[PDB]
Length: 290
Ligand SMILES: Cc1ccc(C(=O)Nc2cc(CCCN(C)C)cc(C(F)(F)F)c2)cc1Nc1ncccc1-c1ccncn1
Image 1 (tube, rainbow, N blue to C red):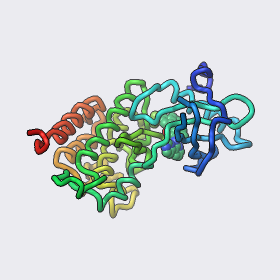
Image 2 (image 1 turned 30 degrees about the horizontal axis):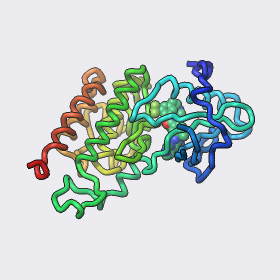
Image 3 (image 1 turned 60 degrees about the vertical axis):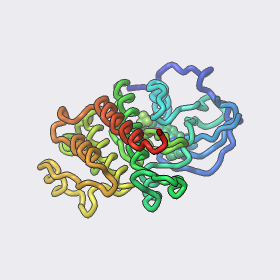
Image 4 (image 1 turned 60 degrees about the horizontal axis):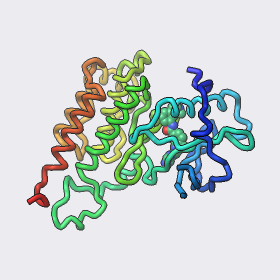
């Protein structure tokens, strides 16, 4: 791709390193570290996530982070794709990529923490279920990720590692697709022939759906991921319905796991379908609408 070579609109993206208050670490990789920070005037004060290139990084590592920055800029804006807010690329400090901060963390861990705080739907008095998750929340998250993937697809992208661990949750129940840089999430064609396409991302989306409606459980419980797993997968064996799913959502997972990639729904069809399911669920209770 050589994305690092793309023109850089510094007036639009460059942020002064001295306008950042660096905080607690959020993660680390071969590239360096990601830390939480407060930025002033990146749009006031706003909390952000900063991916920083380690000192003494190799040329390939440096090139890789710059590439990621240019790719994020190329992709463009979408509510459900982690928002790039700026970068620090000029001399005087490390290369830094700045994104919005999602306070609730990854979806897998978050959902897991709400297992004792979930009900299919609230009933008045609703304060008995304050901050509880409901089927509406779960369908909503599913819908948003589909919207985000439909967007990435429209921009000719292939995610390749779609999973709950790569989805962050921000305020107002808005989720963001990320790629922090996965056999249980791979389509058969990917496992056996290393083939990656938007349709294999759909298969992974199906696993993500299972993760969502199991409230953060690990895929394929009780199964060792080995040649026997691959044999049975290719044969048609699929995960059973998760504990918090609806019949419609489970069939959607099955659809996403069709053996033939061309027969799996497209993200556009998933957006349509999940949107309808969400609307039906959101307007179902007429209690407050007399
Ligand atoms: C700072 C930063 C920079 C870039 C990204 C990120 O997802 N980048 C990225 C990069 C790419 C292309 C490059 C992929 N490489 C494998 C890295 C695609 C996406 C897409 F489209 F899938 F969303 C996303 C996440 C983050 N955020 C982050 N990273 C590591 C740990 C924790 C966070 C975090 C915590 C809370 N709030 C926001 N970010």
